[PDB]
Image (cartoon, coloured by chain):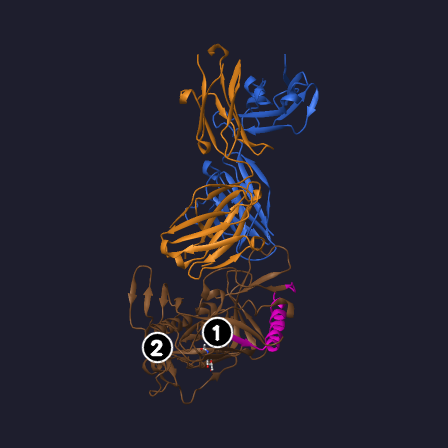
Amino acid sequence: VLTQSPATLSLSPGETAIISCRTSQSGSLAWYQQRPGQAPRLVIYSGSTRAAGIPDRFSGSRWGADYNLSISNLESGDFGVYYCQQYEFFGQGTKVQVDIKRTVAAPSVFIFPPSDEQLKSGTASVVCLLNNFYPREAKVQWKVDNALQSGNSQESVTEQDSKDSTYSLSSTLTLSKADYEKHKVYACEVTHQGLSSPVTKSFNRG
Amino acid sequence: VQLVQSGAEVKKPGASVKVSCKASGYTFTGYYMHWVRQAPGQGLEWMGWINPNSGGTNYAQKFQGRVTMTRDTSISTAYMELSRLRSDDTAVYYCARGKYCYYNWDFQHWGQGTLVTVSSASTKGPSVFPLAPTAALGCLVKDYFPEPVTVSWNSGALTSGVHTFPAVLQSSGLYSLSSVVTVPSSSLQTYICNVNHKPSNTKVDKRVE
Amino acid sequence: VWKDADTTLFCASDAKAHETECHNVWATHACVPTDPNPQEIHLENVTENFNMWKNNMVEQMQEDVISLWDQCLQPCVKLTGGSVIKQACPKISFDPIPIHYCTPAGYVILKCNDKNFNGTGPCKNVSSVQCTHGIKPVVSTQLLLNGSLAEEEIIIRSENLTNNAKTIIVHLNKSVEINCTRPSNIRKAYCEINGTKWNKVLKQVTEKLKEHFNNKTIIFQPPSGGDLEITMHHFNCRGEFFYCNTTQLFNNTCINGTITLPCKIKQIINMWQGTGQAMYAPPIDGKINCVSNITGILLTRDGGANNTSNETFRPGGGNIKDNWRSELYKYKVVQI
Ligand SMILES: *[C@@H]1O[C@H](CO)[C@@H](O)[C@H](O)[C@H]1NC(C)=O
């Protein structure tokens, strides 16, 4: 089949990206770029030949089963996910995303108890916000009365703010109203690079 | 050359879907038409091709028996029907054409795509809950389907400090997202989030006190 | 001494002025008499590259057969989508006759005499001729009718085997007769084939083909979709257009009695010659019968193979120029 590596690629603008692709069958290998929300656009064919409107910055090279797409001097239009292709087969893709380097910034943490209207609906969502932080990696730890909550929540991350280069994150822990009225201390614990030790914002149902 | 597909679709599991693909700017009958899909957490997956003059088809074998490709030359249009839909058929379906010159695989031209969401869930307007108050405040936009919903604040007059998050898919089958804005504690003035869900023709304004 | 080149060729045949069958008449007008004494020179010490998938002669023969069908199979009405024209619907009698293709001055044909030349690549045994062998222009689908045969053993021809969008033509080494009849006394019809000869030839073709897919299990299936001209064995018999269900032909379990195909004759058809449906007059009365020799097949290999076993092949109409390729494959025009 087609094995494309690496899976993910976090890079700054200006740098060069090297994606690899292994085939086991010989023949024309092509590369596609798919930007968020647009149709893929052909970038390279025959392993080494650029398409129309493709600038010099994009280049491909090849060695045996290994295929490389190299994107030099990255710029805003270039970010997305890339696919290698041989006849009807595609690689799994490589998501290449932007992480603008900046000084480390610790998260602001806020916890929100469920609205009354929601409790009236028989469900309870506790929302924990992590504001303006860097780098994107961060850990959230829900604890409900000192009980670790594994798999009772959902996360969502903003794209890197282009201006201050930070991220903001939202974590939502959901429970049945009946489960919710069983326990007292709802805590949210955040670990991050800017924090010398994990930080716990919390609250009591009362 | 242009390729224009029909719009996004929502179906229940077991249902069928029919996507169209209008070609212009070349001799329609002259080039094979392929179809390729991309499901979330999946790579790109070729489904098959049709030979337009013939109406002849080849299908990816795992797709045998449930995919139908046809075309209408009178209007230079290709059609792909996928029957007995399963939830993991949720995907963007594209039609594609070979490079002008031919090898016929180098995919030079793509349709804009047609999104198909397959779910046992039904069209549903959202529920909107306040996230009550250095300080943050927000709206929690819960249990709607399908994507997508937009949020503004104070009818657009409040944009700075706003973060509207990517939706998440819940176990319930319904989507949920949050929108927050940060403000000086000193500012608490009226604040209202304007939430719009076009699929259910739902529009809510929520005052957050 | 010579270089590859394209040019304008002329046709030659044994068509007789007295004969009024449509092809024959077309040939007395378009063509010249076949060479009474052909001359073929083979020379050692030479090597030449051939590519049947890119042979201009195919295009030229194509234009002729389109020309032939335009004045002989003139339909009662034409629906070209943009217009609908009525016109005389002359009764059609035709049997294809062998047509030889020949070069003008200053050019010449090269012939590949490698007994196992698969259709692309360099050829060792090369000869020079002024004209091709006699070729019958049979327009047909799925089955190649009344063509030439492999000298030694069954041969698989394709531009790229891997590329599922490349047409596969199997070229049998021993033909199998197909008897088609429509009794008198209406649109019904039938075909007959000796199960034994046929199935034997299937065993052999699947073994050769497999030979080309690293010994993986080979399976046949009916067409996956498309127009009636493609999904059925389709051909023109005594001016009637037959459409036979071949579902029965590719029957996995028997791998014998004489198997018989259900066929139908149609008055509404998709012209192969280009675009549009043609309407011919109702089928004439009297028993109508064509007996042809199956010499080749057209197959499309299924995409998305995945796990190694079960390549799936569907007899495939592909493009009709492929019928011409199946006979013109071994020749090329070169310029002195
Ligand atoms: C094939 O050849 C035979 C005998 O040479 C002829 O009778 C028959 O009509 C031909 N088939 C077609 C459909 O051209």
Q: Colour of chain B?
A: orange
Q: Amino acid under label 2?
A: Lys
Quick one: which residue is furthest to the right in this view?
A147
Q: Foreground mark, 2 or 1? A: 1
Classed neighbour count for the residue bearing mark 1: other residues with Cα under 10 Å, few (<14), some (14–19), many (≥20): some
Mark 2, residue position: C91
Residue drawn at the location 56% of the way across and 73% of the way down: C155
Of label 2 and label 1, which has the lower sequence position?
A: 2
The picture quadrant where one finds residue C87 is bottom left
Give the percent coordinates (x, y) of residue A7: 59, 41
Residue interval drawn in magenta: C190-217
Q: What label does residue C189 carry, if any?
A: 1
- Which secondary structure lies at badge 1? strand
Q: Which lettered chain is shown in brown?
A: C
State whether label 2 is within 8 Å of ligand 1.
no
Give the percent coordinates (x, y) of residue B25: 35, 52
Residue B163, visible in the rendered structure? yes
Q: Which lettered chain is shown in blue?
A: A
